[PDB]
Image (spheres, helix red, strand yellow):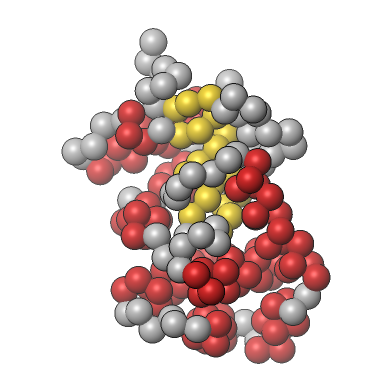
Length: 188
């Protein structure tokens, strides 16, 4: 057929109960994740095609970048708690990978300060238990899908996007296929 198990996607042998409908994993340290988000705009193309009643969830991962990697997961939790994901994603990517001016938790905070988030507001989220559980949620989700690498995307806790079984030349054919495959899986 047009969409095939083992081709554009794979099936988790152990489906995840109560998972987000569309769940993406990434790291701000991840060069491929920079490409996915900042050059290919995969998230944005996926959401442009999602059915009504389907939201996209995006989680950060700890395993790249050591202590800073975990700082970034906690800051992403702060972004989710504050609802400012769409203001910090680009300067976090660019600060870690382009300018490389993000080298400590304080440098991360600066990005939020510069983006209009009050310091008091950021610090209260940073030290909150609400943010601590948001960190734990992200870690739990990674365990639940038995995550091996990033970027990755899972649909309805049952299917894993398989970009290596897709076409690679035209970034745009590749991106459209990725997005089309997510939509297909969402209704499956």
